[PDB]
Amino acid sequence: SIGIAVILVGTSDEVAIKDAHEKDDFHHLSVVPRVELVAMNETDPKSIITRICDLMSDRKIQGVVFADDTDQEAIAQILDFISAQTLTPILGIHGGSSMIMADKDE
Amino acid sequence: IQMALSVCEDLISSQVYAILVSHPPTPNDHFTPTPVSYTAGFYRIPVLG
């Protein structure tokens, strides 16, 4: 079991999102996804760097999924830098994290 | 990794309008300015190498 954490910034309902958190009918293989709902106002880089690199210390996780509902023009680039410095895959889903970029580090 | 933590929690808060990139102790290294120009480039702060 590898913990998967989801982070979202903005106005949203925690219970509505958490209703479908434990809804993946993955009985074929024992994935056991320990989905954790994380909500924090982390637009600034300081909040992101002090939270992303602290998650592994508390909870043993090898995968992070990021979502957002803001129109930031450079959040995707600054969030991509953590992926380059680590080996934990991260996926941009919603908001500025899904904006286009030219190239990625190898 | 500590560069982003150290640069933006100790330098940008001190009202700096220009930042100079350091020099790697080993010339074959590369990641001396790559953390400096990322965090400092968020706020359109000129950086000199």
Image (spheres, helix red, strand yellow):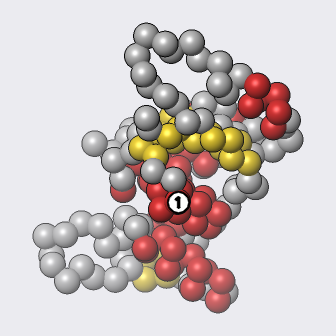
Per the image, the residue denoted by label 1 is: A58
Above or below for A16 versus B41: above
Residue A34 x/y as whole percent: 55, 36
Q: Secondary structure at mark 1?
A: helix
Task: Decide if residue B31 is on the left or right side of residue A35.
Answer: left
Which is more toward the observer, A26 or B4?
A: A26
Seen in the image, is A73 located left or right of residue A89?
Answer: right
Q: Say above or below: A90 vs A21.
A: below
Mark 1 surroundings: few (<14), some (14-19) or many (≥20) residues within 10 A = few
Residue found at the very far bottom of the displayed protein: B14
Which quadrant of the rendered structure holds the C terminus of chain A?
Answer: top left
For residue B38, side relative to residue A74 (left or right): left
Residue B28 image point, x, y percent: 13, 70
Q: Report if residue B3 is visible in the image.
A: yes
> Residue at position x 81%, y 37% from top?
A14
Residue placed at 57% from the left, 12% from the top?
A25
Q: Quadrant of residue A88?
A: top left
In the image, what residue occupies the spot 43% across and 74% down?
B3
Three-letter residue code for mark 1: Asp
Check the residue under mark 1 and report the chain it is in.
A
**Residue at image point 59% right, 35% down:** A35
Depth check: A84 or B32 in front? A84
Q: Quadrant of the N terminus of chain A?
A: top left
With respect to residue B14, does A31 lie above or below?
above
- Percent of width and height locating residue A72: 69, 46
**Image-quadrant location for residue A96:** top right
Q: Is residue A77 left or right of residue A21?
A: left
